[PDB]
Amino acid sequence: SLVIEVMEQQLAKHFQAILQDENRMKQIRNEFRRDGYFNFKNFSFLPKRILENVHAEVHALLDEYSVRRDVTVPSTGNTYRKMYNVNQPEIAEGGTFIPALYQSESLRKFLGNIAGDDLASCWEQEQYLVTKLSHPGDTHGWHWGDYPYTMIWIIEAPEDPAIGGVLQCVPHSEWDKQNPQIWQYILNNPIKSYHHLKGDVYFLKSDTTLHHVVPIQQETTRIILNTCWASAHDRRTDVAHESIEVIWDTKAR
Ligand SMILES: O=C(O)CCC(=O)C(=O)O
Ligand SMILES: NCCC[C@H](N)C(=O)O
Ligand SMILES: [Cl-]
Ligand code: NI
């Protein structure tokens, strides 16, 4: 309670210091909207101490709740999901910093400032998820998100991109679960590829940016936290969660 109250104060001061440079914010909003992506590199998104607390929490959650999954997702053209993961109810049961950060007003206002929108909590069992890629073949195939505003926290990552785990993106698409047309979006757009290191945290426009994680080529450790927010002006009533159900499940396993 008191640690979280102090943490929110440190977050507000951190985000206010970034927002003070409006001319730089214009470029950040530009890049995020144009590319559907913006990376806060080298422990810059949060105060470094708080970020390292998140890294330790993710490691502890994997040590406690890790579940191996090797499935295909019919709503994303049957692309593969081969990973260890921890779902939202498991993170909600043992986590402390991650559930609090998801509800952080200063964090939501800062991301909303970049995105040009108001952030709100998404469907509960998708609010935060963890994935771990380790073995050759582990991947997070081509997909979209059901909700627009996703933050990916790089907990562990190989420094050599040849080992795998590269993120590739096609922005300004959208998700047709019955007719995804993934290859047509790839043919009609250039693909931008990104490599990430431990401490990176990147903002992703997940509902209109087709993306995937290049499969692992050699035994390594790639761990990410996914915090996902809806739009406060989302007027959708019939959002299906078939991808979350098959990869992470909705109950503590
Ligand atoms: O591992 C990444 O960098 C992205 C993972 C992802 O796309 C997701 O969690 O929805
Ligand atoms: N926030 C999690 C997004 C998962 C995505 N719909 C997928 O099929 O992997
Ligand atoms: Cl996504
Ligand atoms: Ni994704």
Image (spheres, rainbow, N blue to C red):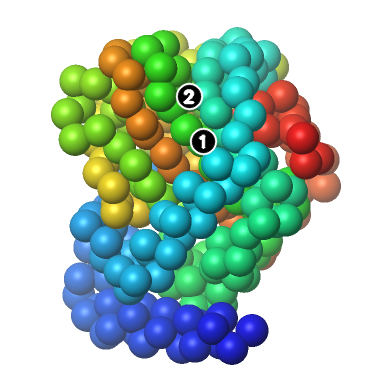
Give percent across and percent down for residue 58: 50, 50
Residue 88 visible to an observer of this rendering: yes
* Residue 131: mark in rendering: 1
Q: Is residue 99 left or right of residue 107?
A: right
Q: Ligand 1: does it lie within 8 Å of the C-beta at label 1? A: yes
Q: Is residue 249 left or right of residue 2?
A: right
- Report the residue at 19% width, 20% height from top: 162
Query: Residue at 56% across / 74% down in the picture?
Result: 104
The local crowd at label 1, few if under 14, some if 14 to 19, many if 20 or more residues have their Cα within 10 Å, is many
Q: Is residue 37 above or below residue 114?
A: above
Residue sitting at x 34%, y 71%: 49
**Amino acid type, label 1:** Thr
Tell me the quarter of the picture where residue 211 sits.
top left
Disc 2 marks a residue whose amino acid type is His
Q: Are marks 1 and 2 in contact (CB under 8 Å)?
A: yes
Residue 33 visible in image: no
Q: Pointer 2: what residue?
A: 140
**Which image quarter holds the N terminus?**
bottom right
Q: Position of residue 154 (x, y in %)?
A: 36, 46
x then y, percent, for residue 47: 33, 73
